[PDB]
Amino acid sequence: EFAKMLKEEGMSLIEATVAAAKLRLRPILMTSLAFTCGVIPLVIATGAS
Amino acid sequence: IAKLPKGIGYEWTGISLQEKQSESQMAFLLGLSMLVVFLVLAALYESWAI
Amino acid sequence: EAMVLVFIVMYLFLHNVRYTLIPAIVAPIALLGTFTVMLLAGFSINVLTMFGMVLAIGIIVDDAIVVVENVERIMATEGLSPKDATSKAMKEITSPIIGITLVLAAVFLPMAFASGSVGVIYKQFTLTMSVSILFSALLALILTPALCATILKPIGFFAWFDRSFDKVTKKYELMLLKIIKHTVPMMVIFL
Amino acid sequence: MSQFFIRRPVFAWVIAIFIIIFGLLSIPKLPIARFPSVAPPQVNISATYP
Image (cartoon, rainbow over the protein chains, first blue to last red):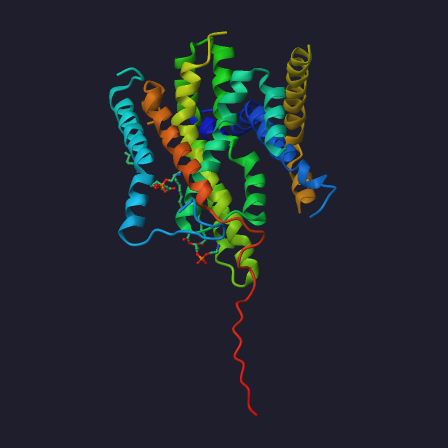
């Protein structure tokens, strides 16, 4: 979505898409790792059930 | 009744049960009403003091 | 334990207690709202609905994570005050948050209507996750802007993390730029 | 817009307070179990014929 907005602003597809990917690295990694670490206790369960 | 022999219980029925229930919830209802009024006023007047 | 781990990771990335508490408090409120909706609908506490909350822990914060990320970035780069930075961040991120919320809520809807006991199992997760996500979206559009504008103030392992993240971000830029040229080899690998 | 609540923190705080206090009130009144009614209901007709 951010790449679409940037390209519509006037930047070329390569520049717009690469800028959108660069700027949104931290949100994506942060919100993926939050979920990944949240489910670790499920994976490493070692007792009943 | 508390002085009666052990193993004997008592129950309130009819009007008595309703009267007991009515006085059981008085404090909670009063507090909830006050809290709702406080929250409404805080929402309206943008402040935690008024 | 999932809540604790999510808080730990948010701390290890944001580096500040405030920045982590702004999104962290959202999850308990969303879960309380889901409990209210469960009472209204007629659901109950059980292993399935609680595994639903465990899975939701991670996703019901993402909107607050994004809003705090953007406000932090604006404050760091443009040097704006918390209020102006928050306003600009919201202006930028409003649409993405609505899109993510609606998509993530809609993905779970089909499972609920499945027939059989499998459908019964699916309904618990669907209700829990969808209600939690919808409540989190409201709490991120409503409360988080105000908290960021108000509580936040103008402004070891953390410095190393920042430097390494900048380096890997530049490396990602370079790698992605290299990859763009080789589009057809990329598509064949995807296939 | 979302700009409404940036300048009105009290109104978002009271909304959050309402949600928290309704959820806390609701939790005690919810049943607790292991699994839901996730099995086909069964009804038995028993007939004794000498």
